[PDB]
Structures are given as C-alpha cells and as structure tokens.
Image (spheres, coloured by chain):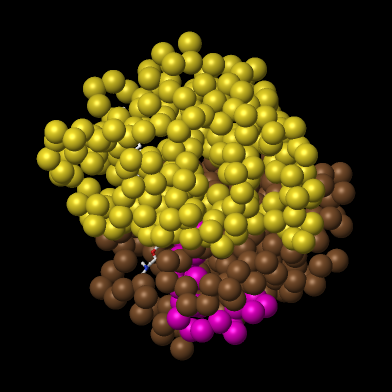
Chain colours: A brown, B yellow
C-alpha cells in the first residue's frame, strides 16, 4: 500500500458540524451565514492539513500561501462532494446541514449546487474511494495554477510526487482498469470549473468580508 | 505509432488568416470584430474536424451538439496556445494577427490573454508536441462535462478511447517519463478555467449576436 496515501488518510481532519442558528428564521441570509461560518472553520483545518503533505512546508511561505489562495475553494468543494456520495440529489455540507433542491433555491445556490451534484454524479459512477479522494485533494492543492509561484520547479516536484502516489495506488488496487489514475485526473477540470464559478459568486455577493483572504492565510500560516 | 494520434494529425485543419480590415481604424471594436470573425470560421472547421474523431459521429446529434457546445471555447483556446509556443509574450491568433500586451490592453483582453499565456508557459516547459496537442483537443471535446448528455456511457467510451491513445503515445515516445500522459491530463484544469472565464467575458460583452450558439451548431451539424 502506498505510504503517501496512508499518510494522507491519517492527516484527514475530523468532521465539523455546521450548527445553523436555531433562533434565526430560515432565509437566504441564514443559509449563506451558515456556509460562511462553516467554511471559515474548514479553512483553518485545511491550512493545518496542508502542512502534512510531503514537501509542502519546505516551499516558501509565499508559495504555500499562493497554492492555498488558488486551491481553497476546490478543496472545500471536493469535501462536500465526497460527503455526499451516498446521498441522492442532496449535498452534505455537514452532518447537520444537508441541502436539498428546495434549500438551494432558497439560498440562491441552485446553479452552483447543481454543478456540485454533477461532480457527485461522476464520482458515484466511478466509485470514488476515500484513498482517491484524499489524494485528489492534495493534487488539487499542488496543481492549482497560481500565477504567482516563486519556485515553479519545486511546485512541479510536489505535483509529481502526488501524481506518482495516485498512479501507484491505482496500479496496486485497480488492476482491472490500468487507466483509472488518468480517469481520476480527468475529473479535475469539472472541479476547477465549479470552483471558478463558486469564487465568482462569492465575490459577486461580497462574502469575503472586511479583511482580505490573503491576510487570512498569512495569519494562519505564520 | 498510435493510429488514433496519426489520424488526428491528418484531420488537422489548415491555417486560417484573420484578415483584420485594413481600412478600419485600430480600436477595441476592430480587435473584437476580427476575433469574432476568426472564431466563426474556426468553429465551422472544428465541427468538420470532430466528425473525424473515432466514435463521435455515432453519438446522437443531440450529444454531438452538447459536446461541441461545452468544448468549443477550449478547442479555440488550445489552438491559439499551440500556435504561440515558439513566441514570447505574444499570442498567435493567426499568422497575420499576433497580439502583444499592448494590443491585449487595447482590446480589453489583458486578463484573458494573460491566462492564455499561462497555458503557453506550461506547455513550453513541457515541450508540448503536435501529436499531444491534437490528442488533448480531442480529449477536451470528449471530456467537456455537458450537463445534457443522453448516452453517458458512450461519451465515457469516447473519453476512454482517446485517453488510451494518449497513454499509448506517451508509453512509446516518452519512456524517460512514465507519468507524462498524466502530466498532460493535469494541464486540462487550467484550460477549463481559462475557457470558463472567456465564455463569461463573451456573454458579458454580448458577442454571441442575434442567433443563439445552439442553432449555429445545429445548422452546421445537420
Ligand atoms: C458552494 C457553497 C459555498 C461555500 C462552501 C462550500 C463548501 C463548504 O464545505 C463550505 C462552504 C462557501 C461559502 C463562503 C465562503 O467564504 C469563506 C470566507 N469567509 C471569510 C466568509 C467559502 C465557501 C458558497 C460559495 C460561494 C458562494 C456562496 C456559497
Ligand atoms: C480569447 C479571444 C476570444 C476569442 C477567440 C479565441 C480563440 C480563437 O482562435 C479565436 C477567437 C473568441 C471571440 C469571439 C467568439 O465568438 C464567436 C461567436 N460568434 C457568433 C461571434 C469566440 C471566440 C475572445 C473570447 C471572449 C471574449 C473576447 C474574445
């Protein structure tokens, strides 16, 4: 069994409850608040998680920040996708916050949650395993295509190392499909597309708040 | 040598000149007109090209249209990227229409053309070959993630067939890097991201015109 995959499995953060405020009337604002508060907590643990990825900490702080800046929404989305694989037309943002179509409509997230469900659909068909999920999260971080990378070569080595882990996993676990690793890689474009739209929506409705995201990753990394 | 790759090479369309109107004063409008007129001509030949891809014609007309609808901007962009690999900070839209930074600024395309140059940068480092380019164009078509596919399984078989061709090519041509096929696949997210932004920009400034894109692919396919 592949050691990087094993390591990523033990580095996996614990479940986080959303705790929607039971005193607040249901509304689009309440849904967005709940999601913002959930994501902020998730981002803190994502930063800690990334430090476990072999080679990530040896990048400059600027490069670590750049990768995180570019990847954070993909990592959040891949999480909700994975959590939702055993459900039907619903998204498990947390065990206590499962969004059906009516809820998504109410939150103004129909189009976005429908795209996320498209990711779910594909991964259900492919029978996405936890091992594959955690490896793809790490790959999405390393492959996030920041336009501000200092050490392009080191970031490529990190991509290489993680891709190798996925290939080695699939070679051992899935001999019935010698192309499964590539199929997994071919799911990344839809994740990127969905993230891109989610981030556009995030800025369009001003969820970023008073303090820029750049400084937030700084505080947490420094 | 891989037959699908060989076939794709012979299916490659001839060069198309942009023919910017020499009587028209240079302006953002002239640049956008030139690009619109270039793309429209390219789209006609792209539709003919897709018919050469093994299995594409045996899909329903609806599925052919769906793949084209979802992929067309990626295919256009991958073309300009490939045409630009031997240039520096300039995009070869056509032999007679090469956009430098000043031109992009003037056209309102700085951000978009900069993203396209990011694609170029990565492919230069990877030493992207024509064989790899034409194969990735076909993969981008098949992997374009339309939300309206009728025969999900047939579209997967098409993805499979093209992925197999890339893997077989790389296995024979690039034994020094057993992971090169996966590296090529890992370039697709940035293409998707760039296309997504280009399409958003395309609709934001109303370049679609009086007739919807759906009917355009119909006419040309029927
Ligand atoms: C898709 C749901 C979502 C977020 C989300 C996704 C996955 C997940 O596990 C948790 C949340 C989302 C919402 C807000 C957000 O902002 C965090 C920044 N702070 C400073 C508010 C990030 C993601 C969202 C994204 C954009 C607009 C509206 C909602
Ligand atoms: C990135 C350049 C570009 C186009 C382009 C890209 C590659 C290429 O080889 C040729 C052109 C572009 C521009 C217009 C366009 O519309 C075609 C639809 N008709 C009906 C006008 C498609 C692509 C463009 C895209 C969006 C907004 C503005 C410009």
Report the front residue among A220 and B14: B14
Whether residue A53 is visible to the viewer of this picture, yes or no, is yes
Residue A71 in magenta? yes
Between A78 and B77, the residue placed more toward the observer is B77
Where A216 sits versus A88, above or below? below
Residue A31, above or below B23:
below
Does residue A21 appear in this view?
A: no
Residue drawn at point x = 33 percent, y = 40 percent: B96
Tell me: A1 left or right of A161: right
**What residue sits 22% from the left and 48% below the top?**
B107
Front in this rendered view, residue B217 or B10: B10
Q: Look at 46% across and 88% down and name the residue there.
A: A222
Q: Position of residue B67 (x, y in %)?
A: 52, 29
Residue B174 screen position, x and y as percent: 75, 55
- Within the displayed image, which quadrant is ligand 2 positioned in? top left
Taking the magenta stretch, the answer to whether it contains residue B163 is: no
Residue farthest to the bottom, as pictured: A222
Q: Name the quadrant containing residue A206.
A: bottom left
Q: Is residue B220 left or right of residue B177?
A: left
Q: Which stretch did the figure color magenta?
A: A53-76
Residue for point 38% across, 50% down: B91
């Amino acid at each position: 069994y592949n050691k990087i995959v094993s390591h990523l499995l033990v580095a996996e953060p614990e479940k986080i409850y959303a705790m929607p405020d039971p005193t607040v009337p249901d509304s689009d604002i309440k849904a967005l608040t709940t999601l913002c508060d959930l994501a902020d907590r998730e981002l803190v643990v994502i930063i800690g998680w990334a430090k476990h990825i072999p080679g990530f900490s040896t990048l400059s702080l600027a490069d670590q920040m750049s990768l995180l800046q570019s990847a954070w929404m993909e990592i959040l989305i891949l999480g909700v996708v994975y959590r939702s694989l055993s459900f039907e037309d619903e998204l498990v943002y947390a065990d206590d916050y499962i969004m059906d179509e009516d809820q998504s409509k109410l939150a103004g997230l129909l189009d976005l949650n429908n795209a996320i469900l498209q990711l779910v659909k594909k991964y259900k068909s492919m029978k996405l395993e936890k091992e594959e999920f955690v490896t793809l999260k790490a790959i999405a971080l390393a492959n996030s295509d920041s336009m501000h990378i200092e050490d392009v070569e080191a970031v490529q080595k990190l991509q290489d190392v993680l891709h190798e882990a996925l290939q080695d996993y699939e070679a051992g676990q899935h001999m019935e499909d010698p192309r499964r690793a590539g199929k997994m890689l071919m799911t990344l474009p839809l994740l990127r597309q969905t993230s891109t739209k989610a981030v556009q929506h995030f800025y369009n409705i001003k969820l970023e708040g008073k303090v820029p995201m750049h400084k937030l990753f700084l505080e947490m990394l420094e």
